[PDB]
Length: 80
Length: 69
Picture (cartoon, rainbow over the protein chains, first blue to last red):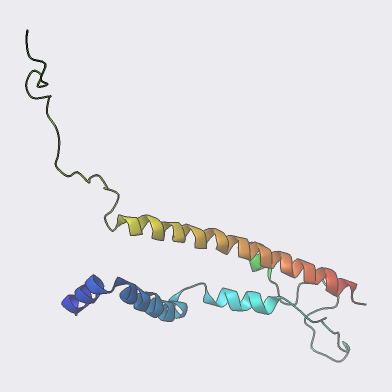
């Protein structure tokens, strides 16, 4: 283990470092705290016109006037 | 007269034959430390700038979607 890695890192540093970049590149996306942010960002960019629905006879939320807060808020991106 | 053959007062001073190839001290692993450091800067700044550019992205899509009707 220690001697094996010392010897493969003595002979072929390019290949060892390559496996390091590889493995760390595999694991790190799982642990890091910032992950969810990227997803929520990517979902926060509309490409397609938001299309209204019949309001009356519904449960009130995501209200008419765009200022009325009841809908989702990306303000967390406004300051981050 | 006297003789004009060459040799002067002895020795011509000293001369240095031996090999010399010194002086590079910046290299421990610490070269990695400064390079990898530079990476660690790049990802920081670039992270920031991409966030900003996303902010601009949403703002532009807002221009369009406000236009649509």
